[PDB]
Each structure stands twice: as C-alpha cells, then as structure tokens.
Image (cartoon, rainbow, N blue to C red):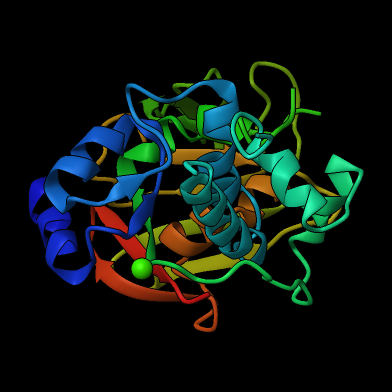
Length: 267
Ligand SMILES: [Ca+2]
C-alpha cells in the first residue's frame, strides 16, 4: 500500500528533504511524505523532467551525483541564469562548455561535488513505473534510441510465447522474432522475488543487444516481461530496484517493498 510506504517516508525523512522520482508520483509523495520534489502534475515540462529522468535512467554513480546537483541547484534557483536553465548554471560552476561531456562527466567516481549539502535526498522507485519507464528515460536524452518494452503473454502456443508487444519469445528465453526472424538475446534474467535478491542471469551470446526479463511474480498487470537494451540494463532503476544491486557508498536502502523501494542518497 503506497500511502503506508510514503507515510513511512514522512517519519524517516524531513520536511526540507527532496524525493527524486517521476512526476506521476509528485503529488502522492508530497501529500504522504510532506517533502519537496523535482516534478509533479503541475510541473513537468521537458526541462523539468530531465533531472528526475537522468537520476533514474543513467548509471548509479551518475544518478547519485545528479540527484545531489539537481536538488541543490533547484533549491538555490529560488534566490538570473539559475532561474530557467539550471543545467547551464551547474556547468559554469564546473567550467564545462560541452553539455554531452559534463553529463558523461558524472559517471566517473572522480567527480567533485563542490556545492554544499543542504538537505537529505531520497529515490523513490515503484514497480508500476516499469510500465512507463520507456517514457521516463526518454527525457534523459537532450532533444539515438533506447529500448524498454514490457509485455504480458497473449498465448503460449507451441514452443513460443506471444508477447503483448508484438514479440514472439522462445520458451528457453534465448531468441525472438516479432513475426520475422531469430535474434539471440544477450542474457536471460528472471525475478523470483524483488523484495528478496531472488534472481539469476545466464550469459547467452555477447554480441547480442536486447536483454530479456521474466517477472515470475509480477504483482503488476501487464508487466510480466521486459525487453531492454544494454543501456536500460545499466540504469539505476533496473539495477537498483529489479536487481537490487546498489553501491552502499552511494545509497542506503531505507524502505524495501514488493511494490516500491526508497533509497537515501549518501552524498
Ligand atoms: Ca538543511
């Protein structure tokens, strides 16, 4: 129950703290937790979405840093450039002229956070977001496609599975065609239990792109499988929520649930 988990968040965290998350949950979080957010029903323009999306789509370390940067610079952006165009502001304070290289800059373990820490930050990552994560991650691109297609079985006739995304998957989980021809999946990944670290990956051809996810116990209707590329596989969302793999020098797990996870930025 979301209200319960976000009411748990209220007590754990502080009124000044931010929760970083997608805007669809902006209001619920502010209501249940009584904390600040980056976006919400009333504030989710492209320029807005970029920051939650980045710290949800990029690699853990990159997301850890943006979380801190975006929060600190948005807060400050309430006292010139810092108003309207917060990414430029932070680039100057890092003397980076090229948007793409600064952003790539963030993935490095050797990135200095000059700006002081002024408040706590939490990541909120609900299961149900998978169904929309494709749209979430799209906003971490300045506007080179990605792939995050979730699907449920329509039928299972023969040794194949008629996935809802027009895809036809083999029962050994090693190929699909989409009504055409075979293309080996990079690896196989099945989630026996999220709350628990119950999963396993089977390497099956390196030069292959798409990963395949089997959600043996999806409590989410319409999300039984996930087909994703190497990038989405890298995201903090997949790695941290689904695979429950995270750096304990970057994040603290303060709320574990079947339905959602909450991490405390430690930086
Ligand atoms: Ca403070």
